[PDB]
Image (cartoon, one colour):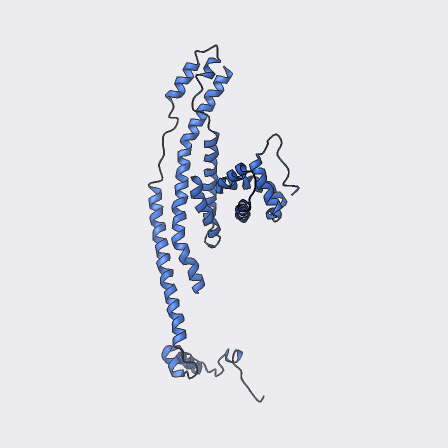
Length: 52
Length: 171
Length: 84
């Protein structure tokens, strides 16, 4: 029973770290969307200009 | 960088192996990894925001459209506005998670010391060379309850007794 | 190994990623991986290397010689990758 208990003890603290970290990462991808639109506009502009 | 978050993530993934509670939790981490890996290659792919008005305008000899698209790009240079939506959901999630985490932590910490104490109790107290059934009747009224229930039932062979203790007979 | 050494047409692959990919097959880490998944593994290993330790990759590229310490780090990295 002590063996079972020891696993759970360590988990309880450390999991909270991952919990935060995971959402933090997701936030970064939101910001990446703003980038994506910047990238997009540049690509489009270069293409129209290339045709000219 | 992003790799710090992810180094803790994958260390935690191979720790998450050691929790069988996961179902789609590992799939959520996998998903955050996917799009995280997408944004870094997006960011590495990135074109310079505007066309070169130095080189790439002086190439064109039809130029009256390079000023148009130069100014149009630099006008609409914000191409998307910011999103911070993780400040309402992350705190809510963090509250339930924190509560549950702390509950688990305190519960198992208590249990560890309870088991430690119980382990000590078996070592430091155990009559077993002179144990009296009176002491067991005192430690559990289950003893008398079962004896009485057996007399009431009218079975004077208690099953299991001879399956881990002997018995003898002449017949 | 034979499955591993295929390369998609008209795309080259940097030397700094040749040394890791080949390392896995050589050390037999990918022996366990089934043939159909070898291809998927290859691309995954590269992304995994880029995320987990692009320090390792950069060291491999620039030092250009694999010291025992670098091979040590690599063994670990492959172990981690294969496990996932």
